[PDB]
Each structure stands twice: as structure tokens, then as C-alpha cells.
Image (cartoon, coloured by chain):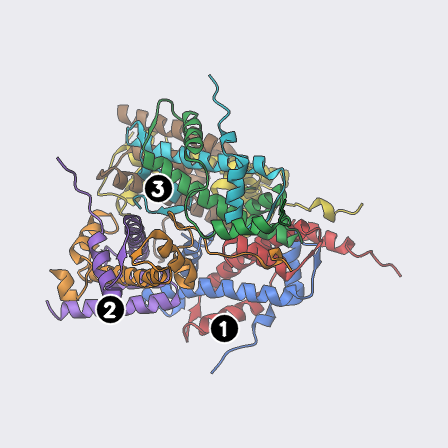
Chain colours: A red, B blue, C yellow, D brown, E green, F cyan, G purple, H orange
């Protein structure tokens, strides 16, 4: 019936997610990933729920800002599409590596 | 035993939403697994420090303060959870 | 005037700030002016941020500063943005900024 | 009867009532404000401690806080914080 | 006569200057620049010679590393030539630029 | 009186030598002035802090230690000058 | 007259002799080693300071230095560091 | 001396002094300077080890700062410990990017 051109819903989603502040990763998958990574460091560990909220707030903030730098690296290479190599350039310059 | 198969709970549409808030229009197919590796390295570095703090307090429960202190350790200070 | 805040004309607690400066292993001895100056700087920056975040709140039709108003505030002010440049404000989001080349022509 | 947890909340509500007398603040917002105040507190105190140590002084005086503020704050914010601090010290000293 | 293809002496100079550690800015121009910048902060000031040496070591290390990152941005844009946009992208990511 | 005309003492061949040590093969013509501005801002930020330290020590001579302390302040720690 | 400035120069030499008896060191390189020790000293000490404050303790004990070393140092470097630390503490208390 | 009793070359006395004179905490335990002095000695030896190696590779008997720099930047973990540090007079590692090489 009706079909939007590629980039139209993408741009609509940018405006949408830049308007809100809610976490974008689903809470239970994230929690299970936190418990797994921590398990591989020390067994039988409990988490305050706020400690997982703090790890998720920070983690999502890190990835948002990293996607910002990644986007600039893509644009720097006259591209519109972010690629693993843009992430890697970003992290290298940031001195994360 | 070895724990595995959880990182994939950070799904393709979730990474996409984060990219959107970051202003990203178009996303290569290889970005998703790459972002998983990045987030694991990040979570590893921070949780390692959090646990180090937890250990030192002789506790079995990781507190929000342990994480906050660890974020601060890495130069990633976080407001709204204590400190 | 019994309180040291009153004697200084501050809303921020000079006594508590003097306590924290001593119980904090900053130096052997803490001068009498230090807590006053510090409590006053703290007050100034506090007011600076509340100003801009009450403004954000009002632009958004709200009676209450929520953390997004603090984030809008900090990240639209160059100097607050810099003071908090390695800081992450829970639940505050980002500034709306779409890159030009991404706009349809 | 839960443990006393100190906060800058009451002062933050004061300043906010001076500057926006009809504006409120949520839990999380106040937590951020409280982390801001602690953060900047630690940063200034730390730089003062270093200044004293660098000059072989045993004492942190308002002069150390002042220089701490000049190294730490950007331009205009420093200017204003310095005058608002010197003003408080001058008072305090006379009264 | 004789002529090397463009880029050969560039590579020779890369190999050469990544082999050595001596400073690459002439000392007196740098010193006069330091004094000029400092005057705009406080008038009538003296500098220890070692203080200027410290400023030059630090400044040059900063510029060398920044040129590394700039080079990576240029290569990122399929280019061999560094351009002001590579520097600006580098500093943007480093968090120096906004 | 207004001070100027010293930054150009950071010459083109000097910026070129720096780029070479950074591994740069080819250099645009607009890079040289750009590198002059960047180096100015850097020195500004560092010398400002250095002078703030000298002032506080009530001195008229900027010491290597003032510079070291300022570099450290800026996250650019330098070894070999009194660290 | 004369003015006294302390440095770790003599101890760096002493250790250099353990690891490389037949090699020496320039003054510049010596000043870097000095910077390095001070810097690492400050960094561990600062972390240990914070650990104490976080836990509401008035004392920095080996246990704070030990945790400090584990927050600070990377992996393999920490493991060895904790060993030499615990080792020297043991040898010290058993020589009282 | 406390160094011998601990078996260190590094001065336990001086480190205990500095920890007290440094406003780190009210009180400094008796094990703290020993542990710290030992860590400091260990890292010292790690860097001297690798930089005497650099010196020998470079046909020198004496460590200059370039040898310390070669040492630190070729070692991953030292490179990371000193990642925001600048080693006067140490230069860079020889590294030309591939695409810049003639084919």
C-alpha cells in the first residue's frame, strides 16, 4: 500500500530517541549479561538492583557517545553508513584501542 | 563450568536504537557483533574494578557505590546513584 | 547570628563543609576561611545549574526539574558542558543534533 | 529506623527556591545535584591539597581554595566563583 | 640531473625522524612564542630554561601524537594527505574540540 | 601595547618534521596555519595553568615544576623534569 | 653552600645492578625513573587513600596498598606486584 | 633498617615518611610502606630489565631515555600503565602505515 523511502524512518527514529532519556536495552537481557560477566570474575555474587541500573546507565551512555564519534568517522570517509572500521578508528583515537 | 551465550541478549534492534540516539542513519551488518565485543570489553573493565572494591569491603553483594567508584576510576564519572 | 553560614551570608553549610575538609585527609590543618569560600563556590555553581534547569523545565511546560532538564541545561551551556565533560547524567539523554549530510535534499 | 544518610538536598532546595520559587525537583534530579556538589567539592579540595603540598604548607587556606578554583573552573565561571568566595570570606572575617 | 619520485624522501624522513629523539622546533622561536603567550596572562615574568625545555618536550610530543591520529583519519577517508578536517576530527574525538 | 607575530616562528619545515615523526607522507597546504592555531591553544591552556601555579607561590619565575604540575593537571604527565 | 634534594637514584642503581650488572644509565634516563617511581607512588597512595575513606577507616594498611595495586595495575603486572608485596611483608614481620 | 628486614633495596623508612607527610590518611599501618616500597621496586626492575635489553639491542652499555621509551611502548602492559605519560627525549616507535609503502 504505502512505503517510505529508505532513510525516512531512520531519520524519524533519530529525532525520537534524541527526545527521550529512557534506557534502550531491555532490562532483563542486560541484567543476565551483567551477572554472567561478573560470575566469570567471582562466583556467588549478589547485585543491588541499582548497581545494575548504574551499569546500564553508564554502558548505554558510553555506547551513545561512541556511536557519535563513529558517525563522524563515517562522515569523514564521505559515507553515511557506520562500519566496524569507524568504531575502531574512534576507539583508537580515544586511546581505548 | 563455562558460562557463555548471553551477550546476544544485546539484540540487533537494541544496538540500532542506541545508534539512533547517537545520530546514526545507516548501519553495516557487521556492526552488531562488533558492538557486542566493545560492550563486553567495557563491562569487563568496570565490573572488574567494582568487584575489586566489593571484595575489599568483605561483601558478597556488589553495591551501586562499588560501580560508581569504578566508573570514576576509569574516568567515566556517573551522577545519580550516589557519591 | 549563631551559624557560620549566617555569618557568611550563605545558604550552604559552612560547618559541614569544614567537617568534610578535616575528615578527608586534604591537609593537616584547615583554615577558617576555606569552608566559607568552598561552601560559597558550591552555592554559586548550584544556583548556576538550577537557574538553567528551571528554565529548561519551564520550556518543557513542567513545574519540576527532572534530570533531563539538568542535562539540557549542562550541555547547552558551553562552560557547564566543559566542567562536566567527563560526567554522565543518569536519565538525561542527548541534545537533538542530526548531521547535515543526513538531511534529505 | 534507618541510618542517617547526609545530603545537600536541603541547601539545593533553598538555592532553587531563591532562583525559581515555583519550581520543583525530582528524586533523580536531586541525586544528580548531590553528585555534582560532591564531585566539585572533591575536585577543588584535591587541587588545594596539591597546592599546599607543592608549597610545603601544612594548611589549606581560602587562598588555596581560590587558586584551586582558578585552575579548575573555566574563565567566566571562575571569575564569578572567585568574587562570590572573596565576598563570603570578607564578611566572615568581619563578623 | 636526478629526481626521486614524490613520496620517497617523505618516507626517508619518516624513517629518519622516528629513529631520533631530538627536538624538531627551533628552540629560540619556541621560547619567544612561550614568552609572548605568557605575557597575556601576567606581565614581567622570567622563565627557567628548563621550564621552556619542559614546555617544548610536552608540546612536541602532543603534536607528534596528534599527527598520528590525524594520519589515521586521513587513511580512514581513503586518503594519503592530511587535511585540517582530519585534525578537527581527531580533536573532536579526543574531547578537546566540541 | 598588543603583542603578536611570533607563532609564525613555528615554521613550515618544522611542522613538516613533526608530521614526519607522526608518520605523515603528504601534507595539505592549509595544515601549517591549522597547526599553528592548535599549538597556540595547547600552549595557552598549559601556560595559563603554569602561571596560576607561579602566582600562588608568589614568584616571578615560572619553574619547570609549575609546568610539570600544569601538564599533569591537563592529563599530559611528563617524566624527566621533576615529576 | 649547598642544598639537598632527595631522589630514588641510588635505589634505581642498586636494582639496575640486580637485573643488568654490566649496564649503566644516563642522568636523563635517571630523571625519568625518578619521575616514574614518584608517579606510581602517588597513584597507589591516592587510590589507597580513597579506599580508606570509602570504607570509613582511619588507616592505610597493606591491605589498602594491595587493593590499590589491583585497581591500578593491569593483570599480569598486578599479579607479580601482589606477590612481591605480600612476600616482603611476610619476610619483614618474620624478622621483627 | 626496615629494607633489609623486608629484603628490599628500596627505602621502607622514606616511604613510610612520605605516606604520613602526604595527607593520605590519619594513620599508616606498618605493612603499608613495606608493600608499597616493594611494588615500587618491582616495577622499577621490570622497566630497568626491559630497557637494559633495549640498550643492548642498540649496542649501548648505558640506558638513555630512548631505551626507556622503547622499553615502555613495546611492552603492552607498561605502555598501558604510562599511557598518558611522556618520556622526555624518547621519540616514537618506527611505524609506517602500509598504504604509504610503494608497491
Question: Tag 1: Cα neighbours inside 10 Å, few (<14), some, or many (≥20)?
Answer: some
> Can marks 3 and 2 be said to lie on one chain?
no
Above-or-below relation of G81 to C20: below
Image side of residue B68 versus residue H41, left or right: right
Q: Which of marks 3 and 1 is in front?
A: 3
The residues tagged by marks 2 and 1 sit, at their Cα atoms, a distance apart of 31 Å
Residue ID for mark 3: F68
Which residue appears at 22% of the width and 39% of the height? D56
Q: Nearer the viewer, mark 2 or mark 1?
A: 2
Mark 1 belongs to which subunit? A
> Can marks 3 and 1 be said to lie on one chain?
no
Which residue appears at 50% of the width and 68% of the height? A34
Residue H8: % across, % down: 19, 63
Which residue appears at 17% of the width and 60% of the height? H30
Q: Is mark 1 on a helix, strand or loop?
A: helix
Image side of residue E70 versus residue B49, left or right: right
Mark 2 belongs to which subunit? G
Residue ID for mark 1: A36
Visible in this render: residue C41? Answer: no
Among the 4 quarters of the image, the one containing residue A40: bottom left
Above-or-below relation of E80 to A40: above
Residue G41: % across, % down: 28, 54
The residues tagged by marks 3 and 1 sit, at their Cα atoms, a distance apart of 43 Å
Among the 4 quarters of the image, the one containing residue A30: bottom right
Q: Is mark 3 on a helix, strand or loop?
A: helix
Above-or-below relation of B9 to G65: below
Q: Is mark 2 on a helix, strand or loop?
A: helix
Residue ID for mark 2: G86
Which residue appears at 42% of the width and 54% of the height? H83
The front one of C42 and A40 is A40
Mark 3 belongs to which subunit? F
Amino acid at each position: 500500500p504505502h512505503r517510505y523511502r529508505p532513510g525516512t524512518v531512520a531519520l524519524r527514529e533519530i529525532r525520537r530517541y534524541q527526545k527521550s532519556t529512557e534506557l534502550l536495552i531491555r532490562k532483563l537481557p542486560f541484567q543476565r549479561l551483567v551477572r554472567e560477566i561478573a560470575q566469570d570474575f567471582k562466583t556467588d555474587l549478589r547485585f543491588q538492583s541499582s548497581a545494575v541500573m548504574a551499569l546500564q546507565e553508564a554502558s548505554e551512555a558510553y555506547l551513545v557517545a561512541l556511536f557519535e564519534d563513529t558517525n563522524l568517522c563515517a562522515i569523514h570517509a564521505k559515507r553515511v553508513t557506520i562500519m566496524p572500521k569507524d568504531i575502531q578508528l574512534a576507539r583508537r583515537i580515544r586511546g581505548e584501542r | 563450568k563455562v558460562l557463555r551465550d548471553n551477550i546476544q541478549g544485546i539484540t540487533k534492534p537494541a544496538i540500532r536504537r542506541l545508534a539512533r540516539r547517537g545520530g546514526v542513519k545507516r548501519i553495516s551488518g557487521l556492526i552488531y557483533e562488533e558492538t557486542r565485543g566493545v560492550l563486553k570489553v567495557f563491562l569487563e573493565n568496570v565490573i572488574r574494578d567494582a568487584v575489586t572494591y566489593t571484595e575489599h569491603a568483605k561483601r558478597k553483594t556488589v553495591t551501586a557505590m562499588d560501580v560508581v567508584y569504578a566508573l570514576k576510576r576509569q574516568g567515566r564519572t556517573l551522577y545519580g546513584f550516589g557519591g | 547570628a549563631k551559624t557560620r553560614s549566617s555569618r557568611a551570608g550563605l545558604q550552604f553549610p559552612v560547618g559541614r563543609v569544614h567537617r568534610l575538609l578535616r575528615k578527608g585527609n586534604y591537609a593537616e590543618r584547615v583554615g577558617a576561611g576555606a569552608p566559607v569560600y568552598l561552601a560559597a563556590v558550591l552555592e554559586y555553581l548550584t544556583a548556576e545549574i538550577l537557574e538553567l534547569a528551571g528554565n529548561a523545565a519551564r520550556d518543557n511546560k513542567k513545574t519540576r526539574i527532572i534530570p533531563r532538564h539538568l542535562q539540557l541545561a549542562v550541555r547547552n551551556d558551553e562552560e557547564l558542558n566543559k566542567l562536566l565533560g567527563r560526567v554522565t547524567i543518569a536519565q538525561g539523554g542527548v541534545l537533538p543534533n542530526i548531521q547535515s549530510v543526513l538531511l534529505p535534499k | 529506623r534507618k541510618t542517617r544518610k547526609e545530603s545537600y538536598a536541603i541547601y539545593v532546595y533553598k538555592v532553587l527556591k531563591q532562583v525559581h520559587p515555583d519550581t520543583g525537583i525530582s528524586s533523580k534530579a536531586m541525586s544528580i545535584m548531590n553528585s555534582f556538589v560532591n564531585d566539585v567539592f572533591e575536585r577543588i579540595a584535591g587541587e588545594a591539597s596539591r597546592l599546599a603540598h607543592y608549597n610545603k604548607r601544612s594548611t589549606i587556606t581560602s587562598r588555596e581554595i581560590q587558586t584551586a578554583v582558578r585552575l579548575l573552573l573555566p574563565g567566566e565561571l571562575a571569575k564569578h566563583a572567585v568574587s562570590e568566595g572573596t565576598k563570603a570570606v570578607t564578611k566572615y572575617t568581619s563578623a
